Amino acid sequence: QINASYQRDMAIALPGMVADTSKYNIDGACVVNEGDVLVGAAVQVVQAQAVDGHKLVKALTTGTTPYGVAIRSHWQTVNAQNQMIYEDGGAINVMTSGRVWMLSKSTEAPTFGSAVKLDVDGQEKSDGTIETTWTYAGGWTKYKDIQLVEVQLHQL
Amino acid sequence: DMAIALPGMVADTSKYNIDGACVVNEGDVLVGAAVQVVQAQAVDGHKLVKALTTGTTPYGVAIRSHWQTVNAQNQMIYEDGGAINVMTSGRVWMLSKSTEAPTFGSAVKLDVDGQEKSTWTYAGGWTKYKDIQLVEVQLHQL
Amino acid sequence: QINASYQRDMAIALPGMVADTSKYNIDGACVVNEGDVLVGAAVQVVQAQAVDGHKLVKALTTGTTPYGVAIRSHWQTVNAQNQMIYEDGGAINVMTSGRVWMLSKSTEAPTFGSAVKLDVDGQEKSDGTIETTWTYAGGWTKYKDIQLVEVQLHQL
């Protein structure tokens, strides 16, 4: 006959979400070429047009320098594979500097200020092959079986 | 006339970044001294700052604030257990122990107290105020 | 009689013009010393005043470190020699971070992300003897008998 009150907390992050409102820069004059990319994964630049002024990007592969991370957008993205993706032949929202949430494949929390190493598919890994100049921003969390890590980005 | 500058005060209005979600874990922090991140909580998002020690990587420089911190001394100080402003990118005046101005664009080195001994770079400002010998430092975020 | 209509396109850029509205930084507390500076060419620092605060700049020279690139302005520039120049003893708008259109004297288009090399006179050249931290941004065009190149400047 006694009443019961309960309490629940929200999750703090989603893949490809901008971590906070610090100094950031979005490179939005790019176009997806040769396939599709995942929100929360790194991309590489294929070529930059001399006159038209659009860069050509795709998912990261072996032996390629990353350029940025795709970020969430409720308008520019299409829903496929139960998640947000960017389809081929369309404008993309690439983040080049700032704090972002990234998909992870590691199993242990990282160290603040250490260098970020990626996997061959553009996802963070504690023992990846591709080396970057980015550093960890401190965040490390999970959303319903999806691991997320907070990454600091600076311009190339 | 007027004094030229004070420790912990931002030099110019160029690109700057200030992290206000921090707290002094232990001891007191002097305004205008470098700080380091002892522990960054993964979920809570707060950074525990401390005065620079031997063989550690600096993070930023504590700045002044007339409301966040008050003190009975002439010089401002951050008390233990209080929110702290730390600037991570931009030009700031800093405490120094050197006596001659170094070359412009040189890479500066930090003492064990958080001071400036004989990566951040020199910006070109070298003044004197009440025997403090401020130095102007450019901080980048890596 | 058959009616006719015509078409013509404008140019893309001008020497010394700011490329786009990405994150940039202009250092306006500078003074020109010992000579004239061409808009769209790199500059060097000869003395930074310790108390007054102004910086003394001049055209680039052999065995020196460049600081930035002067930009266009319709109020701070004098019209001499059928073009815009910065005269001696006047304030100059010097850019130290961002994308800019810069004078060039090479013959082949550059590759994205590679390092920039300068000539003795302060103009971009593919085999110059001066090393810079700057990179190429992909723009490469030509005004009337003038070559231009898009350059990304990082803060020194």
Image (cartoon, coloured by chain):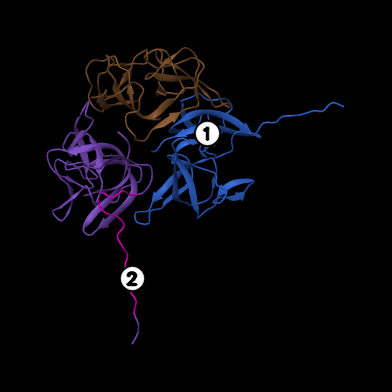
Chain colours: A blue, B brown, C purple
* Image quadrant occupied by the C terminus of chain A: top left
- The residue depicted at 29 percent of the width and 60 percent of the height is C11
Q: Where is residue B45 shown, x and y percent of the image? A: 54, 27
Residue A8 vertical position relative to residue C15 in the rendered view, above or below: above
Q: Where is residue C4 shown, x and y percent of the image? A: 34, 79
Same chain under badges 1 and 2? The reply is no
Q: Secondary structure at mark 2?
A: loop
**Residue C9 lies in the magenta-colored region:** yes
The segment highlighted magenta reads C4-19
Circles 1 and 2 in contact, beta carbons < 8 Å? no
* Image quadrant occupied by the N terminus of chain A: top right
Specify the subunit that label 1 lies on.
A
A109 and B56: which is toward the camera: B56
Principal secondary structure, stretch drawn in magenta:
loop
Q: Amino acid at mark 2?
A: Gln
**Residue C60 lies in the magenta-colored region:** no
- The residue depicted at 30 percent of the width and 22 percent of the height is B108
Q: Where is residue C81 shown, x and y percent of the image? A: 13, 54
Decide if residue C25 is on the left or right side of residue C144: right
Q: Amino acid at mark 1?
A: Glu
Specify the subunit that label 2 lies on.
C
Q: Quarter of the image holding residue C56?
A: top left
Residue B102 image label:
none
Q: Secondary structure at mark 1?
A: loop
Give the labeled residue for mark 2: C7
Give the CA distance from mark 1 to mark 2. 51 Å
Residue A124 image label:
1
Residue B10 vertical position relative to residue A73 in the rendered view, above or below: above
Residue B5 vertical position relative to residue B113 in the rendered view, above or below: below
- The residue depicted at 47 percent of the width and 12 percent of the height is B27
Classed neighbour count for the residue bearing mark 1: other residues with Cα under 10 Å, few (<14), some (14–19), many (≥20): many
**Nearer the camera: disc 1 or disc 2:** 2
